[PDB]
Image (cartoon, rainbow, N blue to C red; front, top):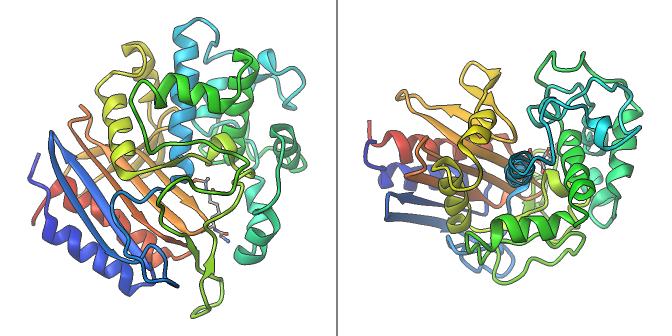
Length: 345
Ligand SMILES: *P(=O)([O-])[C@@H](C)NC(=O)CCCC[C@H](NC(=O)C[NH3+])C(=O)[O-]
């Protein structure tokens, strides 16, 4: 690979701050050589600087943790990707032809209940932040809507799919998702900054605060740091750090977390758009210099995450800006992958 471009990374972060991120930071693990940059503040009220060791909410990177647990269950003979969801969770879904594989690749047609919750950004956050949902509560909210397409037929990203994933994990193992994440992933990879504390609202240890951008342009930011994330759970509630998500995605892509057969299933790409695919709880992004990278994005209120690795896991990058509902920042932060993998023009 090209050398990572730290001057480019620096410019990305500075641009994100100019667009409304209080803080922005990035870590690259380039085959044993670290790159780390940060600009701005973890807490905008106190002025404390952001750093690459600050913990944060990784959002839908959680779907890749959930997918690794499910694929290990496939390896163990406890789950068949082409069985119907209702085989394991009887009566859950209106159509017994919706399969596990379809849920994990967002081809199930299940409506995303968070489109209702977050039609208005700050009121929707204030509505859910202190609520505790069961898995079933969220499935019922989705099923109030019709499915959006026939089983398997269309890619439509939906958090409901990884709510189903959490239910599957808990039913087939008899354990909570926290216990499964801990035993299967956090402990074996020594992810000392990685937690699943749902429904606790506290972020353990030193962390970036999150700042939700309101829908009104120029409006004051809302501190969104402490919330249950119960609206997402196995679709979005993990806490981690840049070092730990680099460790995780490198371990995944280098073949340490499941059999070769299940990793190949995880990387069967469904088209998202002309530069992106979705596997099983895994994204592919195609970068301008002809390199594809693999991992996941996250958005929860106040936190935008990118965490991606090369195909062989030897280079991994995690970037965080502590705002959300700010597409300028979101688009800018994607450029960290360009600078880190494609290098200098
Ligand atoms: P993942 O990270 O894809 C999953 C856990 N996150 C989402 O689906 C996004 C949730 C909504 C995020 C907020 N947007 C709005 O409220 C839009 N009105 C945001 O914080 O940007």
